[PDB]
Structures are given as structure tokens and as C-alpha cells.
Image: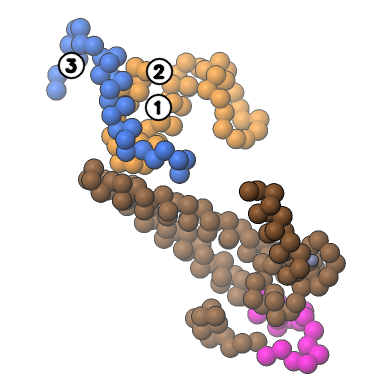
């Protein structure tokens, strides 16, 4: 819960977070 | 930076004519709209680092 | 049609030489069209309200494929209902104006009993069917 630490590799973990739920979105257009 | 016609607009414009902060807010809301329709919570923080 | 049953209306008793535009008939058809338009608007609203509860409540990963499947059908359907309302509204303008009741391609008149069946009819039986044939041919 604390502030982000020096050195944490936020670029990857940002990317990961967006891409995991991709399974729950519809692939048509809706 | 007004709407002179309608229809979706290209992000290349929004950055150019309206500002660094405008396009960043365009993406985050228009992507979060798709996730938030599906009940998926993704803090803007992440979407921002990509921008 | 259960349409006439829901309302206290009985099949219209067309008289022998009965015309087509009197005070009473346009007041009669205006109410039906307005009532018909108001019901669809309430239906579109109920649809949107149901869809948001699904969007607000989050299903479990296992029943996601079933909820997602059902959510897409409503959405498609919802957009279909909105088009119909615009079509009736367009038909409501034809009643008010003076260009309702005839085929748009050829001047032939569309049947009276046929228009009571589908008041949104744009073509006569002959022209409409050929269009569907070209359709299946121009598409596939
Ligand atoms: Zn015709």
C-alpha cells in the first residue's frame, strides 16, 4: 500500500495489467 | 481545436492541435470505456505509462 | 394481431366508398402511431437499464462466456429497436404530409389492406421481392 519504490520496473507491470484481462473483452465490435 | 465536422477523430490531431494532456485523457477514457463495460478494473496509472 | 387486442380497438370497419383522410381517421392513426412510438421508447429504455446491471455486476470467469454471449445479443437487439423507432417516426411524417401509401419505385399504389399489415411498407409485393433476389445475388 505504500508509495512506489525506487527501481520497481513499472513499465512491464503496467503492460501486464492491461493485457491480462484481454481474454474478457469481445473480439467482434459490439 | 473545435469540432468542424463529426465522426471519430484521429489521436494525431488531438495531440497536435489541443495538447499533450488532451490526447492522454482521450486514450485513457476511451480504452477504459471498453474495459469498464466488461466489469474489469484497470487503474489509469498503467494506461498512462503506455501513453 | 395481438396489437389490436392490447388496445381496445376492433378491426377497422372500412365502408364501401370510404375515403382515406378525415379528421377522425388521422386523429385515430395519430394516437396509434404515438402510442406505438411511446411503447418502443419505453422498451429501449428497459433494455438499456437491464444491460447496465450486467455491466455493473461482474460475473465469475467461468460464466463470463455465457454472460458475454447474452450481453452481445441484447446490444445488437437494442440497436435494432432504435432503428425501428426512427422508421415509425418516418412513417409518422408520411401520415402528416401527403406522400404515404404508394410504391416508391413505380407509381403503382400499395394495397390498403396491405398497408394496415405493414404501415412501413415502401414497395409493392412485385418490386420488393425482386430486390431481395438481386440482394442474394449482388451479395453472395
Ligand atoms: Zn412497385
Instruction: Please tell me whether mark 1 sits on a helix, a strand or a loop.
Output: helix
Q: Nearer the N terminus, badge 2 or badge 1?
A: 1
Q: Which chain is brown?
A: C
Question: Of the residues tagged 3 and 2, which is closer to the observer?
Answer: 2
In the shown orientation, is residue C94 left or right of residue C87? right
Q: Which residues are magenta?
A: C13-30
Q: Residue at x 58, y 60 (%)?
A: C84
User: Which class describes the residues within 10 Å of circle 2: few (<14), some (14-19), or many (20+)?
Assistant: few
Q: Residue at x 40, y 27 (%)?
A: B28
Compared with C77, B11 (above or below) is above
Label 2 chain ID: B
Label 3 chain ID: A
Residue situated in front as seen by the camera: B6 or C123: C123
Q: Which residue is mark 3?
A: A3
Compared with B12, C72 (above or below) is below
Q: Residue at x 40, y 36 (%)?
A: B33
* Residue C24, horizontal then vertical, whole percent: 70, 83
Q: Residue furthest left?
A: A1
State which quarter of the image contains the N terminus of chain C: bottom right
User: Which class describes the residues within 10 Å of circle 1: few (<14), some (14-19), or many (20+)?
Assistant: some
Tag 2–tag 1 contact (CB < 8 Å): yes
Chain A tint in image: blue
In the shown orientation, is residue C40 left or right of residue A8? right
- Residue B28: mark in rendering: 1
Please check the rendered image and state whether residue C27 is part of the magenta-colored stretch, yes or no. Answer: yes
Disc 1 residue lies near ligand 1 with CB under 8 A: no
* Residue C10, horizontal then vertical, whole percent: 58, 88
User: Which class describes the residues within 10 Å of circle 3: few (<14), some (14-19), or many (20+)?
Assistant: few
Amino acid at each position: 500500500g505504500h508509495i512506489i519504490n525506487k527501481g520497481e520496473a513499472i513499465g512491464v507491470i503496467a503492460a501486464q495489467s492491461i493485457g491480462e484481462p484481454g481474454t474478457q473483452l469481445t473480439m467482434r465490435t459490439f | 481545436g473545435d469540432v468542424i465536422s463529426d465522426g471519430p477523430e484521429a489521436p494525431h490531431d488531438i495531440l497536435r492541435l489541443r495538447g499533450v494532456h488532451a490526447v492522454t485523457r482521450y486514450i485513457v477514457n476511451e480504452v477504459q470505456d471498453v474495459y469498464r463495460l466488461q466489469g474489469v478494473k484497470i487503474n489509469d496509472k498503467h494506461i498512462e505509462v503506455i501513453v | 394481431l395481438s396489437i389490436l387486442a392490447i388496445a381496445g380497438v376492433e378491426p377497422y370497419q372500412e365502408k364501401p366508398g370510404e375515403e382515406y383522410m378525415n379528421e377522425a381517421q388521422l386523429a385515430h392513426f395519430r394516437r396509434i402511431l404515438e402510442a406505438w412510438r411511446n411503447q418502443l421508447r419505453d422498451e429501449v429504455d428497459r433494455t438499456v437499464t437491464h444491460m447496465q446491471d450486467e455491466a455493473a455486476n461482474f460475473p465469475d470467469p467461468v460464466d463470463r462466456a455465457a454472460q458475454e454471449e447474452e450481453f452481445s445479443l441484447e446490444l445488437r437487439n437494442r440497436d435494432r429497436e432504435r432503428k425501428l423507432i426512427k422508421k415509425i417516426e418516418k412513417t409518422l411524417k408520411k401520415v402528416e404530409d401527403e406522400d404515404f401509401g404508394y410504391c416508391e419505385s413505380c407509381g403503382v399504389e400499395i394495397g390498403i389492406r396491405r398497408l394496415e399489415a405493414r404501415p412501413t411498407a415502401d414497395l409493392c409485393i412485385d418490386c420488393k421481392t425482386l430486390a431481395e433476389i438481386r440482394e442474394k445475388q449482388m451479395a453472395g
